[PDB]
Length: 301
Ligand SMILES: CC(C)=CCSP(=O)(O)OP(=O)(O)O
Image 1: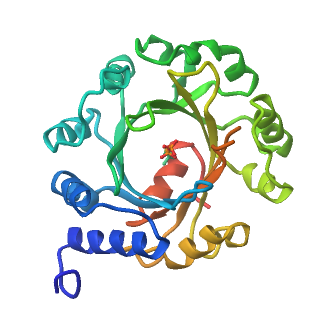
Image 2: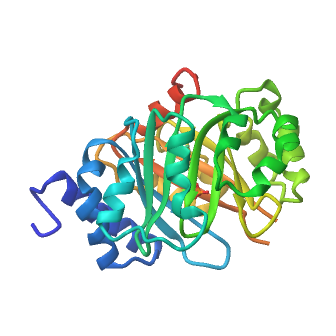
């Protein structure tokens, strides 16, 4: 019953995470997993926890584990620092999450880990606010302010989250995709063409029109948008569009969850020639998907 039988919930989670990673061929480090769980295992037990796989072109599938909770302070930061998971790099990212919590009041936060690396991101979640609130933050890439007209044009006026990616040295702004233009396939063709990204098939465009949340990624090395991502949730295994991609099919059918009937969040990422791939998270305790609809003021499907 080392990894089986009667076990604490946190041990059930660890075993499930390693099983996913093995099944999808994702790399992982036992030392990094243990280090993450020493600090964060209790959080993973009691809050909105998810396991993600994603399939970047020409590399192995990555396996991430992440959680969020409705606390106004950035609790992950202290835990990660103490855990040896978050060292300064001599870079704008070092103070950015602190600046975000100073600049805009948070109603929740979360953290994201790649089990082959350690802590990748911390998220800041405010109540929905005008995007201009972000321009207060000292260490944001200069490219963010420079995209004021782009945000306005594409109805990216309602900021619903921020993140710092310590590994990638980038930041995402997340928008509530409330505008009726965002219910049309042309919107997605247009916003993707504005950046010279890849435009997906019609079948994928017809999925995107239901997206409640759009992320846009900025970095300090370039003036342009690195990639963007459209998030769509599915309330159970069967309603994931399993036919679109083999990773979607396999993960929907086989992802572990403690709750018998989990939903999923899928991120459709696009970039220039990387940046284009799919992310899928299983709602391991069943808390994430309802919270996702609620945070976007949408009835639960
Ligand atoms: C759960 C929400 C709605 C979005 C999470 S941000 P993300 O993990 O998709 O960000 P990246 O893939 O790191 O850009």
